[PDB]
Image (cartoon, coloured by chain):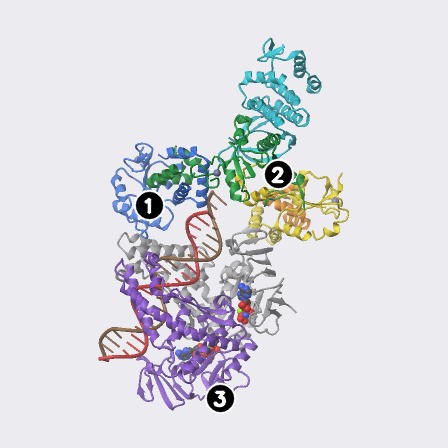
Chain colours: A cyan, B orange, C purple, E yellow, F green, G blue, H red, I brown
Amino acid sequence: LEEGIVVGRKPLPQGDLLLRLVTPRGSLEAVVRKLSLFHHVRFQLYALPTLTQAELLGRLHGLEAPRRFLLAAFLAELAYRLASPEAAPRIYPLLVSGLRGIAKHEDPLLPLVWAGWRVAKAGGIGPNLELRLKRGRLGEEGVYLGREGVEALKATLRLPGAQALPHLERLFLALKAHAEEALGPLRSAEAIG
Amino acid sequence: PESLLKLTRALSRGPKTAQRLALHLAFHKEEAEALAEALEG
Amino acid sequence: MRLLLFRQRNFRNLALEAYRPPPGLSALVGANAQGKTSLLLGIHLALGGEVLGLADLVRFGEEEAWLHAEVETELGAYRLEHRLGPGGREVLLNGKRVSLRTLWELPGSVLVSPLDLEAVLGPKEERRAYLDRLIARFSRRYAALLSAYEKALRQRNALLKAGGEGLSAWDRELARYGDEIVALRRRFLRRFAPILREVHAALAAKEAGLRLEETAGEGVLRALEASRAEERERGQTLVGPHRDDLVFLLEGRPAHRFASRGEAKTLALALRLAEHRLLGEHHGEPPLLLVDEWGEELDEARRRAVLAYAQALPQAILAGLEAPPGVPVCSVVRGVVLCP
Amino acid sequence: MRLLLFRQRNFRNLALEAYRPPPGLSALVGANAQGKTSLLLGIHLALGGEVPLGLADLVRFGEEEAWLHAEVETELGAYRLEHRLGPGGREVLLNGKRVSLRTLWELPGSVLVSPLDLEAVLGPKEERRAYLDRLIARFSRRYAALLSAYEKALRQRNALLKAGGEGLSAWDRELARYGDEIVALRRRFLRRFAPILREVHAALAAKEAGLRLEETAGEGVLRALEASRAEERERGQTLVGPHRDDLVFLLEGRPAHRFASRGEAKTLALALRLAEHRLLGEHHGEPPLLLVDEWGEELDEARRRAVLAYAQALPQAILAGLEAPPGVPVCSVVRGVVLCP
Amino acid sequence: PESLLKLTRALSRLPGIGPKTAQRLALHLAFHKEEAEALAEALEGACRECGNLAEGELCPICQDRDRSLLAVVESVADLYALERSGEFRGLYLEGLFRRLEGVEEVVLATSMTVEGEATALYLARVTRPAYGLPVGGSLEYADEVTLGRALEGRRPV
Amino acid sequence: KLTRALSRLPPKTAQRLALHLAFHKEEAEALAEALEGIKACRECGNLAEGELCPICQRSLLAVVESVADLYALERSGEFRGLYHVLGGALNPLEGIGPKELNLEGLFRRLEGVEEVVLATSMTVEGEATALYLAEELKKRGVRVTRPAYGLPVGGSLEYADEVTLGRALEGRRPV
Amino acid sequence: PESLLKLTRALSRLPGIGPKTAQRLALHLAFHKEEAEALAEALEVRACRECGNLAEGELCPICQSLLAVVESVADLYALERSGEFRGLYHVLGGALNPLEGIGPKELNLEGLFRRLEGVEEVVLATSMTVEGEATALYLAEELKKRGVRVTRPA
DNA sequence: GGCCAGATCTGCCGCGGATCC
DNA sequence: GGATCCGCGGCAGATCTGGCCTG
Ligand SMILES: Nc1ncnc2c1ncn2[C@@H]1O[C@H](COP(=O)(O)OP(=O)(O)NP(=O)(O)O)[C@@H](O)[C@H]1O
Ligand SMILES: Nc1ncnc2c1ncn2[C@@H]1O[C@H](COP(=O)(O)OP(=O)(O)NP(=O)(O)O)[C@@H](O)[C@H]1O
Ligand SMILES: [Mg+2]
Ligand SMILES: [Mg+2]
Ligand SMILES: [Zn+2]
Ligand SMILES: [Zn+2]
Ligand SMILES: [Zn+2]
């Protein structure tokens, strides 16, 4: 038995479904014979492992918004690409907190970026902040983050989230550039325009 | 419910019949007592 | 027509000397295994009826059986005798030896037995055979037509089964016989039904009828032509008078699937009585009627109706465990018959 | 074994709510066309038996579904049986779940007596052989398997013989592998069965009763097959085997299909049924339920008195007829309703 | 061996197990007293106002709930399922007419079984859940009647 | 090549049939002939002899995800409108978006007064597509309707998911 | 269309199929057009030179000192898959039943008689039907006439 | 859905009993 | 007294209803 989130749904031509899940112990891939997206679920795997039982633990009803759904898919994909087994116990609570924030907060982008920066920091891809950040390094090239943006980024990377929220109340572009430099292109990047 | 799961698990020593019987015994105190008596017997 | 006297010697377990039934309704009373059925069977045989193996009718440890009957019809009395044994039957009419076909002309008698229920609750073959023999009892052309049709069908099937050949004359013969057989059957059944309906209405409260199903109602030739492919495939003739079906109906429903014991018994008795009435109206004088075990599986009303109907016949003999009320009665004890 | 309650809905012409027979001897009284036979047939079908009537003709005129329900308790414990008769087919729900019909074969069940037994006693050779086969088949399934295998082997060998030539000894050995087993099983069953029938019939009449089974192949199938090659070649069919045995019932040492009256034949049929009931009750430990239809129709006073005496010592039985036996509880049937005063 | 008779009868009485299944279970439990004792030691481990079964006269629904909403349930399994659901703050047939007092909207939580259909027809504010298509899966794994009802039950949005 | 083709069909039966086909050349040739013989309507999207189906040779329109769904709907018998067949659903994970669908082909057939049934999948992705198409239609001045959410016929309550039950409740109707 | 009709006829004709299954697979292949030509190309190994069995190459894996006789290739693969033993493998034409006219000549008994050399044991793995038992008896009689100790599975 | 078990139905062959020359 | 024929019991082969297992 394991507990995790649903971050990947690949339909199988034979009527089955390919499932992609991450737990506090590491990411995994599973299949089912013949559980909705972005749901915290507790499941029992049998071995690609074949799922046998699944228990629902909560629904995020507010994710049906188009932009909110796109941002949640972006966050989940970035989490999965950063879902190392060692970092999984750190990312999983961060994943849940970010999903709750983007579900509840009026502006999903704020908690989205708040969780994404911390996931990037904890996933071994922490940018070097020592006005434009390029490949995770500040300088005269890249997206102009500005003094306020740099200060908010430093506060988020150093202070806990509670007082990091007021500072951030453009960094998304820098985080996307850093993630692309570290890991390569993103499949979901086409959606946003 | 804890006693329900304990009963379904003892009965499992399929799950749908185990559940139907656990529910029936919960809803029939007399029969369940008689069964505990016969098991002690 | 009156049966004045009847004698026998060494026939089953009978050990009597003479029996003189009175005119009108009569009765017989006995327990189990006493000889009512044997007496009725002997009376039926003595008048030239049909039956048990011919070698099984002789008493145990004997070889010769003798039956003698004296009947005084309207025109004049005459005698009959029968000899049974290893050689065979020796029927002589009033002293002169003669064949049974001569006795076929005489009225004879009608016997009602528990064996008539199978003509109602039995399979298709039994019903068809019963109808065939019932029609044959009235006419002589029917037997010859049936024999010729059977032989022609056998020849045609034998030729068709073993490979192929020219099938032109066999079809013509089969059609020529079937077209007459079907017409005769229709003509007889057009008249038989109303008498049966009236008799059953007298006996009971429901309604009875007959239904005949014909595979070739317009012509044997066309029916044969319209099935050649499957006839050649299967290898048997699939049309003709030898595949018709007869069904007895109680309130518009088949009798062999819904009727009970009492209804079936009443229907069989009605059929026998209708046959008796038709024979009486045909030959010239009604034959003697013999009813065996008349009132077991019937209630009070049906028994009373049966007795009331039988009260009006010129002569009849009833046998059973219980004596009917208000009629002369004779008892049977260990094969002997004694009368008051 | 004991029956407690029977309920129905849209079965034949029946129309009632419930029926609770008492423990012991019972009775039914009714005129013609009332429903005694229908009630007995319904009980027999509900308790897991086999009804000779077609399935599609057991419902009312107009309706399309029937319901049966019985509540029986045994030495072990109570349980409920339920049948859903309809266009699709029979289905059984033991205590609330679907159950295969073969499972009820292990239950006690019931036995039914009807004039069909009387017809079978006085029937041709094939009917008697079929009756013996069906009677033996209720005590083992190995017998049915052996019968099926023997039939298939016989068909194969006959087809081979009808046209052409091929290897023949193989099929001979194949058929002889089963013929001997069938013969031995029949012999053992008859040896165990005869004395019970004799002692049962000794309490209903005065004469003697017995059985006889003559065999075409007593020493062995192979020896009899090799001794009739010319006849097989001339005819083209197998002429030796268990499929040509003859069973005869004897009254005072004479065949019963040529020297017997109605009363004696009915007594023989009843004796056979009672012996089967006793043997089955000994086999399963708990005797089944006995249902008699038209108990005393074609019998005299002494035989009726003898019949009533025997049925009084049974655990539970139900008799039906047009008259009420003296000294027993009586229920009446009128147009489908059963009322007990 | 007379003691086991009562146990066999007790297990026979419950639905879903035949007499031979009960005998087999008893025989398997006769020589396996280890788990028989484990089961025995593990065994230990309705209010008029509601109709809900609970320890004590008042159920937890009676024991933060409103009397405005009352839902009629066919079986207590559905009651447990809806308790695991938790979408009504309100309290939880032939007797419906004389329970109409004090009720301003009637909630119908009964299943769509034919018995429920007949009960609803006999009983004919009152509300009933709609007929529509479920969530997830595949449109090719459905039934024709549901397709038709969803096409004719199509709502405007 | 044979084992994989046989396994693509929706084990032991596949193998026995492949072996039989190997031992029965004529059947295999007949099957290849039927396949060549078999080798979407421009407007409806169903099957057709040549270009247009017999139906084509309309106030109602039903949006559908795939041709199989279209055919299922037609088998239902409760729809005599026209159809527009998309190429699939939106999927960022598969790089599927406005630049991949047939939106422009859709807009060539749509008019002001019309109703478009929203028969998308019952998933997060199908719901997102449904809402997106509905918004695009309300912008472009056309009615938006959505099939009823609720319980399926023959469905038990015990085994229904909490979302289905919650939608049934929220979408309860008077009677 | 008529092409769909003939495709459904072809699917129904082949064994182990349902008419409803045939129709649903016809509609599924109408939905998937690439799988059509994929199956067509995958549609297009011969009899072994020595044994005569279907061989992935030049000899069947049986050839490449225990001998067994089997009705058909299906039971051959079923027996080899479990892999209790390895030895020479032989396959017959079928069973031996005279109802539909299959005698010893219609079978491949003649081929079996060419390679008895070097054989010390033969086991008759045959089905449990009566035809299988008759075939086993005939084979045992023939080999005993030639002379080889034989065994059969329990 | 698909294959088998078991009862019912139809036609052919050998045997017994009536008739003829 | 021999011989052809007519009718019926007995048996094998083909059809058909209702229950079952595999999936
Ligand atoms: N060939 C025979 N030789 C000597 N006795 C015989 C012969 N055939 C039958 N019996 C005896 O006659 C009895 C049958 O007599 P039967 O005439 O049938 O009686 P029944 O009065 O009609 N009896 P039931 O019909 O049972 O009420 C047999 O049981 C034997 O005892
Ligand atoms: N399927 C049916 N639906 C309705 N009525 C029927 C059906 N089958 C038979 N019947 C009637 O039920 C009656 C027969 O019931 P049955 O149970 O045989 O009577 P019984 O009491 O045994 N009579 P009996 O044996 O003749 O003294 C007749 O009136 C039939 O017409
Ligand atoms: Mg008599
Ligand atoms: Mg009756
Ligand atoms: Zn309460
Ligand atoms: Zn079109
Ligand atoms: Zn080889």
Is there any visible trace of residue A10 in the rendered image?
Answer: yes
Which image quadrant is residue G74 in? Answer: top left
Q: Position of residue F128 (x, y in %)?
A: 59, 31
User: Does the beta carbon at disc 3 come under 8 Å from ligand 1?
Assistant: no
Q: Position of residue C100 (x, y in %)?
A: 33, 81
Of the residues shown, which amino acid type is indicated by label 3? Answer: Cys
On residue C119, the disc is: none
On residue C339, the disc is: 3
On residue F161, the disc is: 2
Instruction: Provide the chain ID for the residue under circle 3.
Output: C
Of the residues shown, which amino acid type is indicated by label 2? Answer: Asp
SS assignment at label 2: loop
Mark 3 nearby-residue class (10 Å; few <14, some 14–19, many ≥20): few
Identify the residue at image location x=44%, y=73%.
Answer: C115
**Cα distance between the residues tagged 2 and 3:** 93 Å
**Cα distance between the residues tagged 3 and 1:** 81 Å
Please state if F51 lies on the left or on the right of C156 as rendered.
right
Task: Say if labels 2 and 1 share a chain.
Answer: no
Instruction: Provide the chain ID for the residue under circle 1.
Output: G
Which image quadrant is residue C278 in? Answer: bottom left
Residue at image mark 1: G94
